[PDB]
Amino acid sequence: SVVIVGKISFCPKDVLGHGAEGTIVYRGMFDNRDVAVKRILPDREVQLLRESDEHPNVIRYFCTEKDRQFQYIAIELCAATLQEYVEQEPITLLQQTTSGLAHLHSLNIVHRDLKPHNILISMPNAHGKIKAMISDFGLCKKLAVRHSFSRRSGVPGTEGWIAPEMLSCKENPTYTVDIFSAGCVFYYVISEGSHPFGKSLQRQANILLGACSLDCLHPEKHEDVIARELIEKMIAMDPQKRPSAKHVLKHPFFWSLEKQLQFFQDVSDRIEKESLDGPIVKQLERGGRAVVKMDWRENITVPLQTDLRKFRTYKGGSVRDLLRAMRNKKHHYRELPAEVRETLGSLPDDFVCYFTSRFPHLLAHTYRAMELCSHERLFQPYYFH
Image (tube, rainbow, N blue to C red):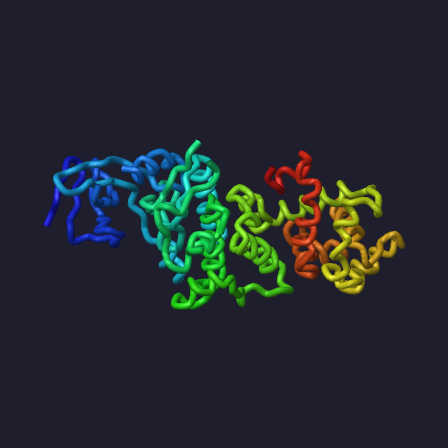
């Protein structure tokens, strides 16, 4: 069978999925191109889609057609959904989803339903590159010229992905409802299918109670510490403690190894020579010696330990002095003894991993302590203000 409405051609046997309120999406043709065809029952969600579709990570819109009962919306055809992708890069997909989410928020649009099933994996482009993309704007809302929106409409969203302030308080929900859903999506991808609040049955109840567990993030593993620090943020019960999508984009969770090492360099250069009694260095050392293991000279390889004795000025209980050791061995790296270059580098990638692996809380601790400088132009790459 074949249905032709205007320029839109689709075979009713081909169904990508079923929406809500009789919404069905088909695989179809528009202007001799493979497309998805969304048959709805009638405007808001279309114009919001049309408005935000210029972003690479937002689904592209082509045409709308109408017959007696239905409106037909031709949109970009994708390969799959993020949910079914979890069955065999993940961080790039999350970054792409967040960038698309940040584009919506910059237009004063709240998605209000976010999950793995809503996120789509694009078909490969001319270069064979694949990207995550936001779709299903049906529940979207554009805020008034108000930074919040009322609950008058209902409880939009899918069970277990809904932020707690939606189901319960004086404060109206705001863009951070999507940040909560995104945080659950972040863990869903990292955990390879597990959810912060666990089983679907009790999932939404545990959200209302604020009971969450991350069992896949090791406390002593660097990659997991950064992911936990970000993901514990954004799912926080208190919505005003959640970061904006732009804040999430700046987080070290997305940093390459060069950016991490450059952050450590700029921090070390920023705090030397500051006053050890001053706010900056006091903030950096406050939680120290737990991150440092309380002597970091004993926790490092001996070839570097015997190369650090050139200065008694290095104090094993100081985070600052640990960052100064890293700064110095990076700048002098090529001149170091081959044993010290091999036990450390190569630069930048294996060099920064030598430390972060031995000091898993170093990057996370330093990142939070250095927010006092977040306004300064030196740290603007690493923070959002």
